[PDB]
Image (cartoon, coloured by chain):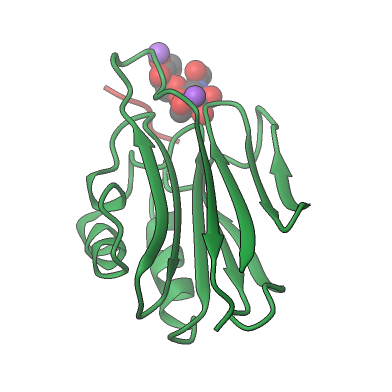
Amino acid sequence: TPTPV
Amino acid sequence: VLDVEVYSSRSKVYVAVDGTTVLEDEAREQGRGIHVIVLNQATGHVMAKRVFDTYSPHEDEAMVLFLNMVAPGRVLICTVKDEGSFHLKDTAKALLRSLGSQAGPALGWRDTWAFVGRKGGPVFGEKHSKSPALSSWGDPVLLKTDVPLS
Ligand SMILES: *[C@H]1O[C@H](CO)[C@@H](O)[C@H](O)[C@@H]1O[C@@H]1O[C@H](CO)[C@@H](O)[C@H](O)[C@H]1NC(C)=O
Ligand code: NA
Ligand code: NA
């Protein structure tokens, strides 16, 4: 699950 | 009228109607995103309750598809737990704007947001707080507003 940045 | 309370924050959401809490979620591991509640506009009874983790990819599409099938006239309640903007895309944003929401379309990273409005009619209340820094959250907001029974 993508996270910034 | 219905006494409606809607709370949005990093760690917790809750919604109450006429003194009865119909949603409370303070998990760390679950419940992130935009919580959506649909009330019967004539009774205040909760017809549906959902949570769309719009921090995560494609959950905003599910929220749109859910909102689409709500009958015009229902009362909508929205509230953010933790983060609801990361993968909130333009279509979902535009839809919230068409629902009369000012802050929904403008929702940003770790902002807080609480909203109560009729689908097809006016907004009854809305609050929003902006995160001041990337590792910070918007200030919790507590929206307490009257909703007229149809
Ligand atoms: C994504 O992960 C990064 C570390 O790998 C963090 O620095 C970022 O702030 C993101 O953190 C995630 O943020 C969401 C939304 O507030 C939160 O629900 C997650 O728990 C959080 N994940 C981590 C590992 O901190
Ligand atoms: Na907060
Ligand atoms: Na961080």
Query: On the image, which quarter does residue B124 sit in?
Result: bottom left
- Quadrant of the rendering where the C terminus of chain B is positioned: bottom right
Q: Where residue B115 sits: x, y (%)?
A: 44, 53
Q: Residue at x 63, y 32 (%)?
A: B12
Q: Where residue B116 sits: x, y (%)?
A: 47, 59
Q: Viewed as shown, does residue B28 lie left or right of B120? A: right
Return the residue nearer the eye: B61 or B112.
Answer: B112
Q: Where residue B105 sits: x, y (%)?
A: 24, 52
Q: Colour of chain A?
A: red
Q: Is residue B137 above or below residue B105?
A: above
Q: Colour of chain B?
A: green
Q: Viewed as shown, does residue B84 lie left or right of B147? A: left
Return the residue nearer the eye: B148 or B128.
Answer: B148
Q: Residue at x 29, y 42 (%)?
A: B107
Q: Where residue B111 sits: x, y (%)?
A: 36, 32
Q: Residue at x 32, y 50 (%)?
A: B88
Q: Viewed as shown, does residue B130 lie left or right of B18? A: left
